[PDB]
Amino acid sequence: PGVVMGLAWTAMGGSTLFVETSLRRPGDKDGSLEVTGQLGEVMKESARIAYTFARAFLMQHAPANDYLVTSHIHLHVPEGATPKDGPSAGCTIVTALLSLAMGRPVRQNLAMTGEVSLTGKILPVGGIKEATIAAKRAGVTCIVLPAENKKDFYDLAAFITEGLEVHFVEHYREIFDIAFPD
Amino acid sequence: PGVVMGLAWTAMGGSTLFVETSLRRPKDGSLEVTGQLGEVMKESARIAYTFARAFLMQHAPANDYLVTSHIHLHVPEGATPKDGPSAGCTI
Amino acid sequence: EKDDKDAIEEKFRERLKELVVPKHVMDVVDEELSKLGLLDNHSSEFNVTRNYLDWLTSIPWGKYSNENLDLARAQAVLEEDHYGMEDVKKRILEFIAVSQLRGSTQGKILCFYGPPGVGKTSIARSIARALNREYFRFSVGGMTDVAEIKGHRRTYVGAMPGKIIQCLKKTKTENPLILIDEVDKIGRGYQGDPSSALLELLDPEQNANFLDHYLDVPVDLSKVLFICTANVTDTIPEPLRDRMEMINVSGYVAQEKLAIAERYLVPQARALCGLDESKAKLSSDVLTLLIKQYCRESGVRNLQKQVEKVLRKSAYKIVSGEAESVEVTPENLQDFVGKPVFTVERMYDVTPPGVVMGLAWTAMGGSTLFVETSLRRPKDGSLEVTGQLGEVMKESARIAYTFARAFLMQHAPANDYLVTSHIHLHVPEGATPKDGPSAGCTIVTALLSLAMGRPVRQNLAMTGEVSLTGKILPVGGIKEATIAAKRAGVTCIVLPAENKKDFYDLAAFITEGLEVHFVEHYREIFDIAFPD
Ligand SMILES: Nc1ncnc2c1ncn2[C@@H]1O[C@H](COP(=O)(O)OP(=O)(O)O)[C@@H](O)[C@H]1O
């Protein structure tokens, strides 16, 4: 729980990244989020946007849950030596925070990517070909992509697409059902 | 509610941008501005926040939403940098 | 081949007979002529020898333009060629008088600085005409290469002498008038620093012998009137400032702009458009309307473009056959220029509490400034400053805030607004960067007006640096600020007492109609801003 596999663009055929969340610390005080790793300014901002939406999404889904409001959460992307940037992992951060807050592991062999706004809308991201190739190399079964990237995904070669269950989403509410079927 | 469409200038012509605000937390309120916003755009948010806080006093005195609550302000497409006081009234 | 070369040698020798060639130059001619004698016409080096020797013969040696030394005639030329510019005209008249006493031509280094469009470049042509000199103009703003000043090496293929050397041939005299433009806009460069070359040009000791890179011989650059133009003096390099004599040209008020447009701008644009006075008519009201609404600069550069546009459309109208004669009345002005560009002279017609009008000065020209204060929130208060404020400007706000708190204790002890409230201070037009302690006293008035809830006296503009104890310090650009204040239609202007010299150096009509107050401490400003 608290670990979600993501997709990243790399010159060496792309790669898949992970997002790890953990409790940093065990009445009006509020929690805080710390982001570690060589994250760029755009990537750091996306974590703040994801953190705000994750808090808001929790009130509607589970008002009694106050894990994301009071607790202090540490977010780390492993392999900190390599620099990371881009809003690609915005939706991955939301799932990691939600999984940690709800204490439920995300669906196995599931990878997601795509920029997310603080209202929950999923925005298209570049490097669809690299992300899809890295997903197959990582041996994932389900891949979540923005709905606006449907043309990019279907423009790829036939032999790098079959065998992959791809989900196209517009809002994070659809990602929540896929990530946490229950 | 909390989302307003604005107008912007780009190299490839005009563009339309949205301004979305949300509650950061469920006694002084604070405003956080996200996105690759420039110094001029960041300052215009402070001016807009001050005026909107003052405008509510003369319009809805009983409404204390802006003075106490914590509001997060984000302009979508965070990868693309933005600057200018053009979006002052949209905020 | 030799016979053709012989004719080339003979014609070149004839040209140098009139010139008083220096001792070290004639030997250079002789050796080049000797090399030309033994070189064939088809040789590549023959062209270089032929061209270089031509340049040496073309440059005058000891030939001086016939200067005019009549004070009355020169003054009449200056008055008929330009309006105003008394300080510039006085220096030129004094220049002629000194030359008369000396009994021979002499040179000087002069600098004209002011807002663009004032007439710095145009007066240079009038001065040369009055002085019976030759006018030459070149610019150094944003220039990084020093080779342009002195040319390139002779052995280099496709190399030409420098602009000063090129100036000598075209002017055909050793006593020309040289104009340098955008001196304040020069900057440091990686390839080379032309500031060192400019220092030698403007140094009376160094310019006596100037070394180029093509002719490779010293040239007497003295006895040459050097005129340089700039927008501001602060950005001019310190060593260059000392060698230059600073003469200030200020902007023009609305009544001054109409006189320039009626007498100079309109006739010049009409003449170059092929029209006549009878066919094309521009009244005073349309010219007044163009200045008030279609222009905002302190100069007349933008006004000239608007006037030229009107004549261009009028010339097209008569050619197309719409009318034999075109009269530009205010009713049909929109058919020529369109909707007015500027509709409001000032952002705040009536200042609410916490709003005080200020004055700002730039290289662009004078400008008006506003300071707005508001309650950011309904143990210790805080002040937030917005806008593109510089480091100096932000610090002045801190000084003003501290003094404003102290002033309220001694004036309204029961009032704790400035200590127990969070106040946001904003200077509108946040896109434009702002810097300088000029608005120090303006910030104090804005904070005091907001705390007391009393609007400041209408049509009042103030400027001047304020100290921690309340002392008012002098500020620069008083002339530019006063012109902008007059354009903004203010009635009362508050200035530091140490700036009295700058304010009274303005023209009589500019000062007239303005209620100026000179202060040394902010206590006097409080009474003026808040009479009750
Ligand atoms: N007092 C004046 N009398 C006559 N013409 C003037 C006067 N002031 C300005 N002008 C006109 O305005 C124009 C100003 O342009 P110029 O001075 O060359 O710009 P800059 O100052 O940037 O070099 C000139 O062409 C000049 O004819």
Image (cartoon, rainbow, N blue to C red):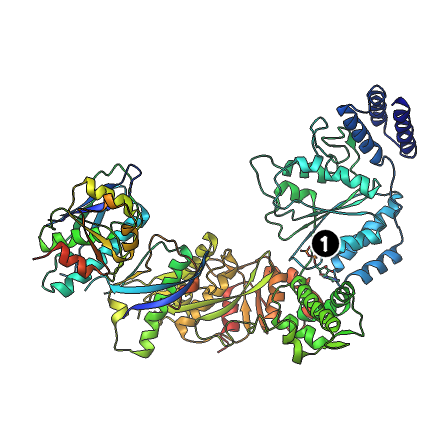
Question: Looking at the picture, does residue C364 appear above or below residue A26?
Answer: below
**Residue found 85% across the figure and 36% down from its top:** C60
Crowd around label 1: few <14 · some 14–19 · many ≥20 (10 Å):
some
- Dividing the picture into quadrants, the one containing residue A149 is bottom left
Left or right, C522 with respect to A102, comes to right
Does mark 1 have its CB less than 8 Å from ligand 1? Answer: yes
Q: Is C127 left or right of C397, judged from the image as shown? A: right
In terms of depth relative to the viewer, which is nearer, B7 or C369?
B7
Q: Position of residue C81 (x, y in %)?
A: 80, 60
Q: Position of residue C84 (x, y in %)?
A: 75, 63
> Is C483 situated above or below C216?
below
Which chain does tag 1 point to?
C
Quarter of the image for residue C453 reads: bottom left
Q: How many marks?
A: 1
Q: Using the rendered image of the protein, determine whether residue A113 is visible from the camera's viewpoint.
A: yes
Q: Residue furthest front?
A: A158
Instruction: Name the residue tied to disc 1.
Output: C121
Kindly state the secondary structure of the residue where label 1 is placed. helix
Ligand 1: quadrant of the figure: bottom right
Residue extending farthest bottom = C331
Q: Quadrant of residue C115?
A: bottom right
Q: Position of residue B28 (x, y in %)?
A: 26, 64
Q: Nearer the viewer, residue A51 or C489?
A: A51
Taking the image as shown, residue C385 lies to the left or right of residue A60, namely right
* Residue A23 visible: no
Q: Which amino acid does label 1 sit on?
A: Thr
**Whole-percent x, y for residue A146 in the image:** 25, 55
Q: For the C terminus of chain A, which image quadrant?
A: bottom left
